[PDB]
Image (cartoon, helix red, strand yellow):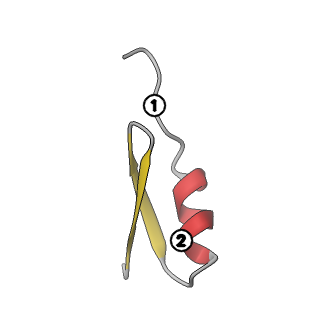
Amino acid sequence: GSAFCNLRRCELSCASLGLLGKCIGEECKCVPY
């Protein structure tokens, strides 16, 4: 595809829980660090 997910759009959304995020295409996943 020509377009992909933003890292802030996962790192902020996982910081709402209290941890870091990483994003693949559109799917955001949270990690402890």
What residue is disc 2 on?
Answer: 14
Q: Tell me: residue 9, above or below residue 20.
A: above
What residue is disc 1 on?
Answer: 4
In this picture, residue 32 sits left or right of residue 17: left
Q: Amino acid at mark 2?
A: Cys
Q: Position of residue 3 (x, y in %)?
A: 47, 22
> Where is residue 2, by image quadrant?
top left
Q: Tell me: residue 21, above or below residue 1.
A: below
> Where is residue 28, by image quadrant?
bottom left
Marked residue nearer the N-terminal end (2 or 1): 1
Q: Determine contact: label 2, label 1, CB under 8 Å.
A: no
Q: Tell me: residue 1, above or below residue 18.
A: above
In terms of depth relative to the viewer, which is nearer, 13 or 20?
13
Residue at screen point 62% across, 65% down: 12
- The quadrant of the rendering that contains the C terminus is bottom left
Residue at screen point 54% across, 63% down: 11
Total tally of numbered discs in the picture:
2
In space, the residues marked 2 and 1 are separated at their CA atoms by 18 Å
Q: Position of residue 6 (x, y in %)?
A: 54, 43
Q: Position of residue 7 (x, y in %)?
A: 51, 50
